[PDB]
Image: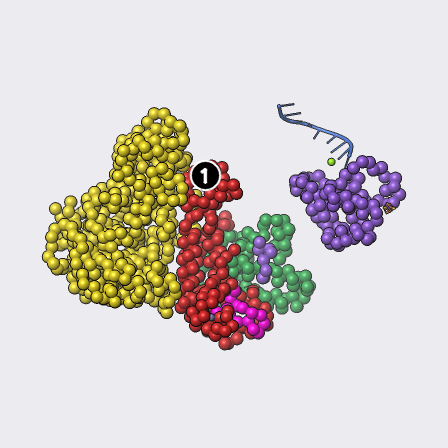
Chain colours: A green, B purple, C yellow, D red, E blue
Amino acid sequence: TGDRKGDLYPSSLQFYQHPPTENISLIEFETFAIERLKLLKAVENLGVSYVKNSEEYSKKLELELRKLKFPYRPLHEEISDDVYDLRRKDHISHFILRLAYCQSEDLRRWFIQQ
Amino acid sequence: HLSHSYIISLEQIDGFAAKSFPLCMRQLHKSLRENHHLRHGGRMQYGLFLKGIGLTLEQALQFWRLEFTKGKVDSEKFDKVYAYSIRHNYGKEGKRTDYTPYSCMKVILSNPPSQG
Amino acid sequence: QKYGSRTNRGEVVTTYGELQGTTWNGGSGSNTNVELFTSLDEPLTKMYKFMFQKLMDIREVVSIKIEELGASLKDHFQIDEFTSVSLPAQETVTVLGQIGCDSNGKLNSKSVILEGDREHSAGMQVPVDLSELKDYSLFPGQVVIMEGTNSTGRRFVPTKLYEGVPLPFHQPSKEFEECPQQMVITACGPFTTSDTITYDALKDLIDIVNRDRPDICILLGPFLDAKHEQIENLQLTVTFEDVFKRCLKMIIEGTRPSGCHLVIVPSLRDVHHDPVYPQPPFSCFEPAKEDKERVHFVADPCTLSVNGVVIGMTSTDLLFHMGAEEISSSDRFSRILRHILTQRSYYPLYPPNEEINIDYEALYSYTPMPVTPDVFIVPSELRYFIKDVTGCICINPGRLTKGLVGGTYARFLVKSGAMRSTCISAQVVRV
Amino acid sequence: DCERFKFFCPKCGTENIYDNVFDGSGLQIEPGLKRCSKPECDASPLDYVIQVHNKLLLDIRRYIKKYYSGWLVCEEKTCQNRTRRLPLSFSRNGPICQACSKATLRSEYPEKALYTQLCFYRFIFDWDYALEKVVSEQERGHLKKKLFQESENQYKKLKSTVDQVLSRSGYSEVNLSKLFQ
RNA sequence: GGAUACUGC
Ligand code: SF4
Ligand SMILES: [Mg+2]
Ligand SMILES: [Zn+2]
Ligand SMILES: [Zn+2]
């Protein structure tokens, strides 16, 4: 909690219920959108290639999450600023992709699945 | 465009019409490509034949849409009218029966063709 | 070479007001209070996001400009009702609108159109026939009220052109009644010769400042001209920001002995600054702790208060811009200056000249003239002058450098409540 | 539809067109500003990075001036009226052309055009983006070593200019409250 | 190609 943080992101996992209210930059918008698109495409490819309970699936998904810097593991330390940042990413990116993936039923289904 | 962000074929049908298509289908295809429109009997016969060769519902829909759109008709008109017929030929609606392709006996003894 | 060997150094090329001695001296900014004119509208003091103009927003801004000026003029003239410009009129009707040219060229008496506001005319235009108007002076973007008739429904024929109404002058408070007269030296760019980047004229002006110890020094851009031959052809070995920083350091440090309040006004020709009008103040230089109270980075245009004296200033060459478009029935500069004062905007020309980028929301918010200024600094490529237009002393000090040869600056004395003679004396002098 | 970055070599005077961060394929790939386009010319544009900065600022000024010129063209082919003046008479689609009174005036250089031009100038200097997206695997490996750190730093500095300009553009903040409600 | 409805003007 360095400068402008709060209790807005208690846990890693979330149901994505409350839309973000912040003012972000266009560069941040684009970066978050593309990064989560990469994450979801990786999820889809790994689901097609491997069994979702397989250990290969878990290893590859962890590698992708680490590469794109998304929250995937808990931390019993506290809400570190870096962690906060990651969670914020996740929360905003999700809703951005919602805006991207609500035009057509097909798209909707795909999004939901991933 | 995020979804499109980098991070049997219809075309060969014409080729088949050169060699494999029986003369009936060859005539129907020639007329279709000459005028981009077929009377009801031709539509039924050619649709059933293209179902027989293996053209999937999506493939047949795409082919008929592309062929008819050139005939100076509204794009929405196709989905309004001919989509149901195309679906029915594949047993998708109505009684929902997988209608078999016409047999030569049926074609000979089916509706007698007339002018046009 | 030519500049360094000039022989007319210090020559007074123009004079106005009370005669003064051959030498001018100031208070070194001792009993001086310089601020931005505190009006209802907030001043432009920081960058505003630009490059995003909706045509609807431009329409709204122009329409509200016409509507507001017309409302003030209607109250002043006791006009009963305005009529739609486009509708036919067999009898005489009063119409409010703005002038324009029917084509892209320069306005002439046969190419005048009147465009009404959204409230009274739905934004419709009408051609204007100036055959029945005996005296007129029109420029594009000028908000006017005219009495005329439109018998054919296709051509408006004005018969009366209502005169402009300037804003009232400022009524100074007594807080500055006992303050002495203040000396102001004003100069405008370019500050370096066409073939040099050494700022020799600026050094001479700084020497003059330290010699005369004025109370305020108003420096108007450009400080790093975009049209400088060295700049355009990319012969500079240092970044634009570095040259501008060096120039500002020279100005500020060199004026330390004089203790003179510096007012820096940007120019649209500043190659290192944001190219948008109204121009935000410079923000790339942080004065030392010993010069923070002396340096004022103001916006273009600026309305300054100096011990109660209101000075309007703009770096934009308003006179050159409007002289190319003003049409008159029969002093041209005095007419243009009166037009500027009566329209109550520091840039009433619409469409603007080709050399100025106008953000119309910022123009609406930061170009209204709060009052009629006591002194109006309007540097121009045209000849230097000191004119008295409707009681306002309009000073064009020229430009410090005119090509290869040295230019001119101006010095004037201002005291609140003098005699309306707020400008005791003024002089355009050679560098 | 965006203009590419034109820089005249100070030594030879030949125009260099830059449209990507990297030029060439395989191990022969290097940053565009490393070598001149003229084989006989040994001058490295990376040496004259002050001049590149100045030319970039001049180009940005040129594009901003083009946008604020406010040129409008009638969308009707048979009219194609070109005017600087925006009329207050509007239809549902926008300004009504005063030459024909039946068609809409469209901006010759809309805001999207300027935004895309600035984004392209940022793109042609985005080292990290080029490495991730544009560059291949072997090329990425060859470019992710030393011997290019100085070029990387200069490219970062040059991208800082376009980033600064874009930060001052209203076409640079996204209000997520307005999007999600 | 056919069949079943009911709006309009
Ligand atoms: S209907 Fe049968 S016999 Fe007649 S041309 Fe076609 S395939 Fe040959
Ligand atoms: Mg029919
Ligand atoms: Zn070269
Ligand atoms: Zn037109």
The secondary element bearing badge 1 is classed as loop
C32 displayed left or right of D173: left
Q: Quadrant of the N terminus of chain C?
A: bottom left
* Residue drawn at x 77%, y 42% as measured from the top left: B43
What's the amino acid at mark 1? Answer: Ala
**Label 1 lies in what chain?**
D
Residue A34 picture quarter: bottom right
Residue D105 painted magenta: no
C220 or C353: nearer the viewer: C353
Which residue carries the number 1 mark?
Answer: D99
Residue D140 in the image: above or below residue C406: below
Q: Is residue D16 visible?
A: yes
Q: Is mark 1 within 8 Å of ligand 4?
A: yes
B32 displayed left or right of C7: right
* Residue drawn at x 79%, y 44% as measured from the top left: B28
Residue, far bottom: D147
From which residue to which does the magenta span run? D20-33
